[PDB]
Length: 158
Length: 217
Length: 228
Image 1 (cartoon, each protein chain N blue to C red):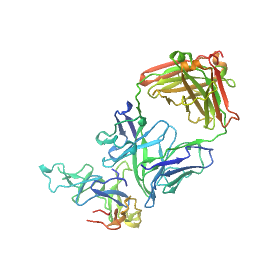
Image 2 (cartoon, rainbow over the protein chains, first blue to last red):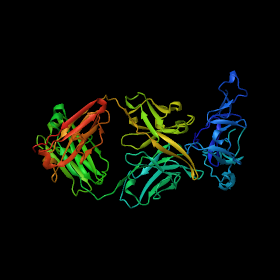
Image 3 (cartoon, chains in turn cyan, green, brown):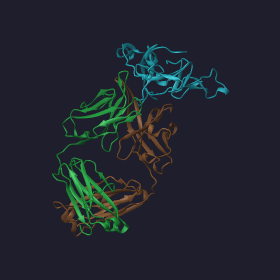
Image 4 (tube, rainbow over the protein chains, first blue to last red):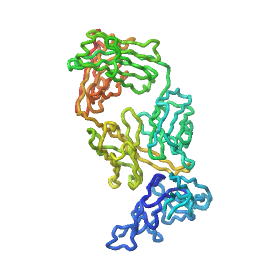
């Protein structure tokens, strides 16, 4: 599952970290797949069967195949006992056996002399395409995203 | 969509000397310091393979002689020392609004000028019995590809009733061959007598003309 | 290895519809975005459509918008292309392409790293017809320097392709099978020629073997030299 700069996140927007891209949901929505966000349910019952209850999880509230429930959130199983710090854990389709690596917050990079965690400082060139003339690539709270550069109503940059 | 236009259409190169391919886009492919343009090579009988990505970066496994430069709407692929294995069709592709390929540039082998051997074939008895008549003008093993075929019936220029096709460059002697077919009804064929194709080529001082008389050869 | 196999092509009339299929093997199909790319005879590659792994992101070329629809079935490791309102300009070889995306340290880029063998789509009003093979006989008017030229005219067939061989594959040197041309009748025509020593024209037989699978037609034509 690979998200590109041309991915259209449904009810969401593209964010970039040191080594990857993902879709972040609008408001309080939950990821149903790598690129769509839907409304979640508060409790799992007969009326909410097979409905989204958390990111990559439906009611049975078990995580989808290939994930595992750690700290009440669904994380890939290869990211189980992998700690990163100043960043998140992801995986790449490059290796045959899926391996969990660290993708760091903007300004940080994998520190090779620190068990490949996110401690070393390093720039990351923004790869997002904010083609609208009212949006530009900004760095917010550790991630890259397209945001307004001059005036927005409350949510459109025009 | 965004329009991509390359030049030249065919680029003859002698192995060892450099080569350039131009590629322009109908609108700027630059955004945030990235140029969204890639280069692909389709060797004969093989799949296309990535060469250059984001304007100037070589893909993993590309020789250093291949390089890409340019920005915005003006781009150029440059081969410093052309090897013989680099023949094929080169495409530039814009990735700003996925996707659009250029029309392709055919990289071919440059050789010495060769004149075409010209032969003309009258229609067969079988085809005449069928009710039609096709005359075939054959140009064999010439270089370069540029060649003009002119049909004349009783020394009168024909137009819009002939069709030609050209073979790919030969893998051994690096020449081309061309076949032109003049098609007429059995009636129009039996009306006239003299049939000829006039070939103009760079390797001919004067335009060669091959002809025959109906009922003769 | 990665293997993409396209199917579903064939013949269709203008206005008609066709549904292409592409089955992916050798990799996890549900992890990759995919393309459809075609190439018309005597033209370059033309990208048609892109589809993400979760089918949430889809793009089309302007030349096929509204007429063509892309979709995938990750359960069956398959990918489809519905083609409606087909015009003659849609006649091409259609490929499905795997689209890798690398998060490289010099920028993120696509890599069309796998291409199927292709499937041929012919949009035309013509009906399937086997070829008539006419001889291009050698004579003094086709000889030059101890060398004689002869051939076969493969005329008025539909659709592509035909396969021409000489002397059941024994004779391969000096052969030139030209690309077919599309005539006004909607039927194809090509010629295949071979160069031989002019001395052998009396003591050697030359037969062109023309095969046209669409019409289930096989024709072997012996090319007799002429006395002129």
